[PDB]
Image (cartoon, chains in turn green, orange):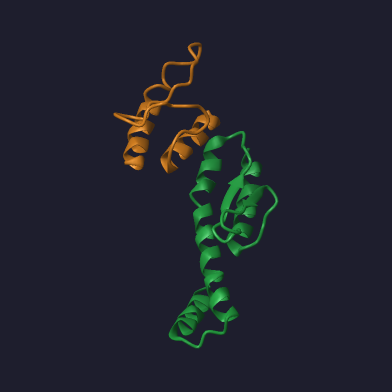
Amino acid sequence: LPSQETCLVEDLLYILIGVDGRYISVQPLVGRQSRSFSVEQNLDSSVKELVNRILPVATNYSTVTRFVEENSSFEYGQVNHALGAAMRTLG
Amino acid sequence: ETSLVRDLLYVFQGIDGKFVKMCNSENCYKVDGKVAVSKSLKDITSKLSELGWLHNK
């Protein structure tokens, strides 16, 4: 059991980097910009549910690294383009 | 023994662990479904319920 927890923890740490894992699969909702991550069933359902509290963190991390990708893709000169660079620095 | 030590970790973080406990109110009482075991798990897991019911509130 705890080794199956540990490789799910390592899959979770890749998901928070912002990259697709092995057992945690990524489902597109609006174009996989609001990523509803879905892990498979586990023999212990509880430790799976502790991971379920953590997939909204990479969901919201995917929203703001793609927010600062969007405003520079149209080369905005406005002050929102300088606000997003702080978000790049916080990222 | 050790599986009951792991089972209390999961209700301490949240909702039910190894087995189902079917109570989110008035305490999160643990049901093992075993009678041939000793009668000394029901009171320890009664103490683990007041820590888990206070956690989800």
